[PDB]
Length: 148
Ligand SMILES: OC[C@H]1O[C@@H](O[C@H]2[C@H](O)[C@@H](O)[C@H](O)O[C@@H]2CO)[C@H](O)[C@@H](O)[C@H]1O
Image 1 (cartoon, rainbow, N blue to C red):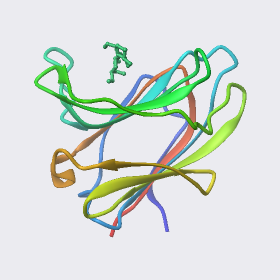
Image 2: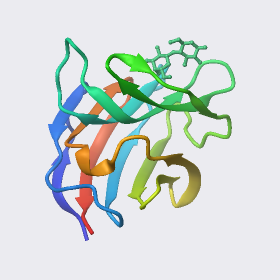
Image 3: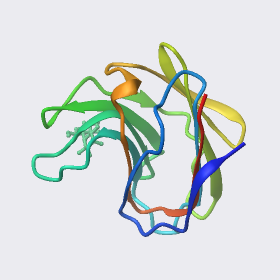
Image 4: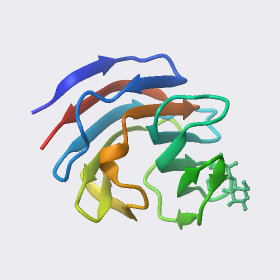
């Protein structure tokens, strides 16, 4: 029901994903937003190069300034694509969360605390994703996977 679990990773976190993100796969991320957070992000990456920066198939980016939002996008050859902004965000400073990223055939389906949050259509085949990055102001209790 959950495997390859990593606990209290240091942020910034970069880790290799154990198996392939095929339709049906869940990525489960539990954490807490620090009282002073501006933003954090979960990036599903093709590799871990820093310079040049690895491509990001799915960038999921809660932001806390202003009214708060989540920005999602894809990074290819160090250039961002079209931004998808979700203004109804469940994240709050000083509150804990369970993010479930469900890989479907045509998109990611993301829920927080069991409530649907957003959809993100695949722009790169998810089979090419091999690295998970978590950056910014966030505390992560655990990262787990359930494949297929
Ligand atoms: O698209 C994700 C990417 O956005 C960058 O910031 C954008 C911003 O989100 C956009 O709404 C604003 O109007 O212009 C900025 C130009 O880049 C971030 O810098 C980056 O880290 C990603 O989050």
